[PDB]
Length: 68
Image 1 (cartoon, rainbow, N blue to C red):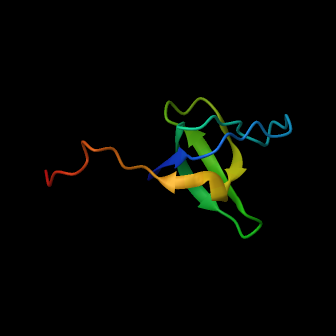
Image 2: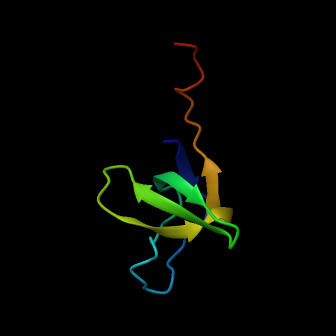
């Protein structure tokens, strides 16, 4: 799966269907839905929950800018 970066805080409502984020957090994304929500998983796989698709931006580290 691809990795996405939280561009905004998402403290959410408290729901266990929600994955609360801080800015700069990095997650996997398995599903986007038309409601505007994305199904995010932490990198260690410990929690799974929906997040605002809008907050989620492709992760680019500056160590990724080399061919191999």
